[PDB]
Image: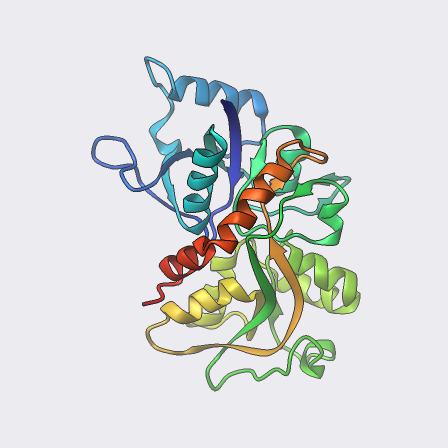
Length: 287
């Protein structure tokens, strides 16, 4: 039996957190730590304590994780006979090349701080050069979130984005594959967006959705934006434009991991037996 330390990132509906219950446990979820660290020794010490007599892990670090990716993780752990420790990435980023190093999930895999990364993690060319990804368990275009009767956009080639009018505010999430895409493909658009980019998806959505409005459009994975539109009561939100920058989501592992092919095989079995349909309908609230 293997023991894997898994890093995740909170991104609805793939991973959510809530507080531990009145007895300190996680009835319908997975106990995880939110310790805000990228230090491997610190995580060893915390998890060691968690699993021992005399658990002295500071209560503020304890959370319950749940979501599409946690259901998937649980199934993998059962089929592949491993147990796992689960923690939330300290910088809250998916990961990019910044100041001579990889940040976020990518960084924790490359430093050996995590054994595997499980969340809405995009498989792109730059990351594929440095970490392993399994076969994808989900696929998504990038998308553009706007208000109903607000900004209209044809897609990523809209002149509104490339010769923006003064005060036209649009952004994406920092250190993500969406940012990588814009940086690589539309360098001058990237430069314009820098002042508008946000730390995390919920910030971009709030800035578009809530008053006083802070973004006119928010660029991010359509699977995530679609989820936000679907839970919007008011019906004030739309995703607009042609698809672009389509990427799979996959589980990240260190490069040339002997685990990758085994996990990919199970992901393929799960897809071809309806399990991804089951998870999609549960978590996007179909039916």
